[PDB]
Amino acid sequence: DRLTNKFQLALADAQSLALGHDNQFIEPLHLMSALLNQEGGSVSPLLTSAGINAGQLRTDINQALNRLPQVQPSQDLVRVLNLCDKLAQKRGDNFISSELFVLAALESRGTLADILKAAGATTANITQAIEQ
């Protein structure tokens, strides 16, 4: 799609994570975990730059993943990805990058947004990190 190759690869990993954890749906949480674990990925350094502890974030995200029902993208994920698209359009980006997911997730309510807020993320410090 309009997604960067790195973002597409993280999505594939998110699917593997959901499968490996016996979850029926790939949730924004799965993608965040994949992005946090992506060597050379943009998400971890973006968070560190925004003043958010990426290490503790993956722990809280893993805790949330551990709470999901066990038994394929969820509508939650489709929704957040749609906002990523709109955000890329508003910022004038040619493609949808991983950093936008952090911003879109923060503005999409639900568990991931709650975790990000508690971790110190705000539309302001994430947007600043993105522009930087």
Image: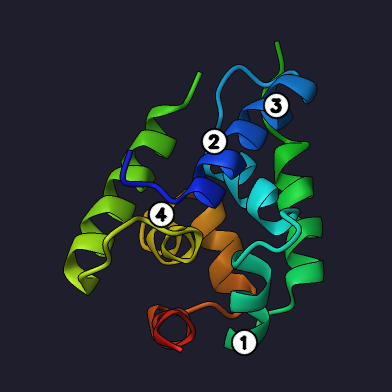
Q: Mark 3 points at which residue?
A: 16
Q: In this view, does 13 lie above or below 110?
A: above
Q: Which residue appears at 60% of the width and 43% of the height?
A: 10
SS label for mark 3: helix
| Three-letter amino acid code at the position of disc 2 | Glu
Residue type, numbered disc 3: Ser
**Pair 4/3: label in front:** 3
Name the residue located 39 percent from the left edge and 78 percent from the top edge: 123
Check disc 1 and report the residue beneath it: 49
Which amino acid, mark 4?
Answer: Arg
Which is closer to the viewer, label 2 or label 4?
A: 2
Q: Where is residue 18 in the image (x, y as percent from the top left)?
A: 68, 27
Instruction: Give the distance between the C-alpha atoms of the residues marked 4 and 3, in whole angstroms.
Output: 24 Å
Of callouts 1 and 2, the N-terminal one: 2
**Marks 1/2: CA distance?**
25 Å
Q: Quadrant of the N terminus?
A: top left
Count neighbours of disc 1 (C-alpha within 10 A) and say few if under 14, some if 14 to 19, many if 20 or more.
some
Mark 4, residue position: 109
Identify the residue shown where x is 73% and y is 71%: 54
Say which residue label 2 marks.
27
**Which of marks 4 and 1 precedes in the sequence?**
1
Image check: 90 left or right of 32? left
Disc 2 is placed on an element classified as loop
Instruction: Identify the mark nearer the N-term, 4 or 3.
Output: 3
Amino acid tagged 1: Ser
Mark positioned earlier in the residue sequence (2 or 4): 2
Relative image position of residue 87 (x, y in whole percent)? 26, 63
